[PDB]
């Protein structure tokens, strides 16, 4: 089964698992299917993908998941349900998306990343090319020339950057896409092998724990909030993405942050701080 | 004429052209499982019915005309990432790699249970009243709450339901990770969500570069947030204002603001007064 069919199989699984009820009319409205094709899709799911996981409930005039029901196409993350609904309605321009009634999603609409920059940066990552561009940083906020060999575009959840060799500092660094003036241009200067970006290829395990300033009842709640399996979250990450992962989890890194236990219920275990 | 699946192929053509500057027929064929004949028919359709002569053959595929404008998508990079992320199954990963040269930092949620979503969502749709078991940082022992939920909210970090709390007679935010077992529908008359004043009242927050940064530094913050007058104006519901400020990593306190390079973006001092008390909007 190819993309079209699988996306419908995925929608059947998600409606049943997260809503607890699947009616053909929802599938019809989502995909513009006939009632016949929608019914046949539910049959294919209940026959080929998740055998007898769905039970017709004539009362609720719909299908419900059996108590045995486990997803087979999706992970059991609620992220899967939000991603399905968001793909049916694009509102990436909105501060607050409303993919369906009774659901609001807080977004960060990004206007600052130009297509002409992405086009060049992505081509240079694919070609392992070198770029000449105009940049500004907090350290050096006057526009200046930079020569970079990019390997990977990165979305942090807040900002876009490219991981690139800087030919002046001879270091692998993170370059903000919002801070590139005009169109980068390809130059015939030898690029550095991305396999030499140690921080990028080296993995570390971050251990996040409930804030020690919380009482033990409050700590049990933090374990629940983060679905911690054994009183911690262990997150394997590339060294060069570790800082961004911690900010994505809103983890306390600093002493004054960890002191505000209500604001920062999650801290990085000290050994890892080093 | 075009249903979801055809509209997805059209958007994909447009986003590859606009963001990558090149559309290779093999990319289409692999993404949607098309023959070269179906792939070329899709390009012909976008080029005929959607964006007349926007694409030209050249590379085993097509390039945007110099006058190329997107017709199906806003010029937000979010649309490109959304399209790519829809094609692969990576909602579980710390770091998604939706294509070989793009890494996305994600927050996979491990705490929201489907039996809770099933009951809360149905109750939102039905305007029902629920009894449930809840714990807060204030009262971290399990206790009963009686709620009339109206909206599920994802903040970018956590999931909550906006609901009327029948004991406190106040609309509050209940974290979905803090419900134990399955909520039960009860006979109590639900409360009209039209009475949630904080949900219905819109406000406008003003975000500025951190005044501790020098003039040159402040100009880059303006470039980062596409705000060339020096102010970013955020219209938002009062009950979502704190979540918006957090999603933007904005300083709201003096102590926060004092750290310029951690908080380059700050809330205007005169707007602090318009904000609710965060940890009074949270259920007990
Ligand atoms: Cl790529």
Image: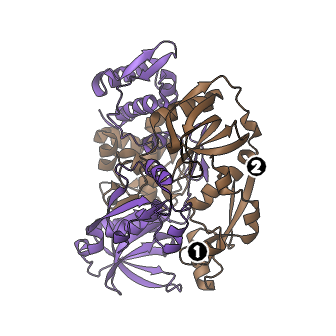
Chain colours: A purple, B brown
Q: What crowding class fits label 2: few (fewer than 14 Cα within 10 Å), some (14-19), or many (20 or more)?
A: few
Tell me, yes or no, if residue A156 can be seen here. Answer: no
Name the spot of residue B19 as percent of width and height, x first: 44, 59
Mark 1 crowdedness (10 Å alpha carbons): few <14, some 14-19, many ≥20: many
Circle 1 SS class: loop
Residue B160 % position (x, y): 57, 45
Chain identity of mark 2:
B
Residue B226 visible, this angle: yes
Residue visible at 61% across and 54% down? A95
Left or right of residue A157, residue B193 in this image: right
Q: Mark 1 belongs to which subunit?
A: B
Q: List x then y, in percent, for residue B187.
A: 66, 22
In the rendered structure, are the residues bearing label 2 and label 1 in contact, judged by CB atoms less than 8 Å apart? no
The residue positioned 63% from the left and 46% from the top of the image is B283
- Residue carrying label 2: B201
* Residue B186 position within the rendered picture, expressed as x and y whole percent measured from the top left: 62, 24
**Residue designated by label 1:** B264
Q: Nearer the viewer, residue B253 or B4?
A: B253
Q: Earlier in the sequence, mark 2 or mark 1?
A: 2
Judge left or right: residue A67 versus residue B162.
left
A144 in relation to B266, above or below: below
């Amino acid at each position: 089964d190819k993309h079209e069919v699988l996306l419908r199989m995925r929608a059947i699984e998600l409606l049943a698992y997260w809503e607890g009820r699947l009616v053909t009319t929802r599938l019809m409205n989502w995909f513009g299917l006939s009632r016949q094709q929608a019914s046949a899709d539910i049959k294919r799911y209940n026959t080929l993908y998740n055998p007898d996981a769905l039970i017709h409930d004539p009362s609720v005039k719909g299908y419900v998941p059996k108590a045995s029901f486990q997803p087979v196409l999706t992970t059991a993350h609620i992220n899967e349900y939000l991603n399905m609904l968001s793909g049916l309605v694009s509102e990436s321009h909105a501060l607050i998306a409303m993919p369906e009634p009774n659901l609001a999603a807080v977004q960060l609409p990004d206007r600052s990343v130009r297509p002409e920059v992405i086009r060049e940066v992505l081509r240079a990552c694919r070609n392992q090319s070198t770029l000449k561009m105009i940049y500004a940083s907090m350290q050096n906020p006057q526009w200046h020339e930079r020569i970079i060999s990019p390997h990977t575009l990165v979305y942090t959840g807040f900002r876009w950057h490219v991981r690139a060799y800087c030919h002046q500092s001879k270091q692998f660094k993170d370059f903000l896409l919002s801070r590139i003036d005009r169109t980068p241009v390809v130059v015939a200067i030898e690029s550095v092998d991305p396999a030499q970006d140690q921080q990028w290829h080296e993995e570390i395990v971050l251990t996040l724990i409930p804030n020690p300033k919380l009482n033990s009842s409050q700590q049990a709640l933090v374990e629940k909030d983060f679905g911690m399996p054994d009183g911690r979250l262990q997150i394997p990450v590339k060294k060069a993405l570790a800082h961004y992962t911690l900010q994505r989890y809103q983890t306390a890194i600093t002493l004054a942050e960890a002191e505000d236990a209500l604001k920062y219920p999650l801290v990085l275990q000290r050994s890892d701080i080093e």
